[PDB]
Image 1 (cartoon, rainbow, N blue to C red):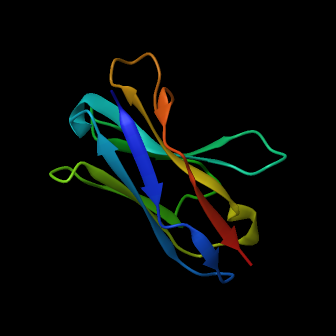
Image 2 (tube, helix red, strand yellow):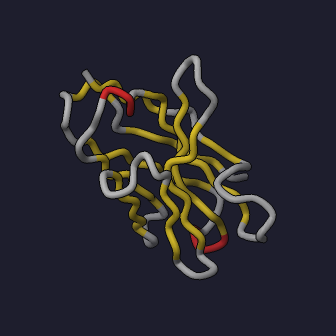
Length: 120
């Protein structure tokens, strides 16, 4: 079955950088939309990025455009979130999330355990 595991969270300075990794098991990346969703206690979850293999587009939340960048290592089946210019409001648990690429949902059906990012 689809399984995801995030890593790389921690405490980072204001305006700093951090690179999260999501390792996968059970599928090839090109069959799925994949990306990142975050949730801070007290707020509903917020999509951060989502990648579609139908045309290779990555969608980003307006709040992170230009600061956060998604990438994949297709051979290693691992995806990444490169965060730059971190702000205190970026503090949240970050999940990598995926859906089978059939047009009905996107970065929704499966998620990992999450990794905490805390910005001072």
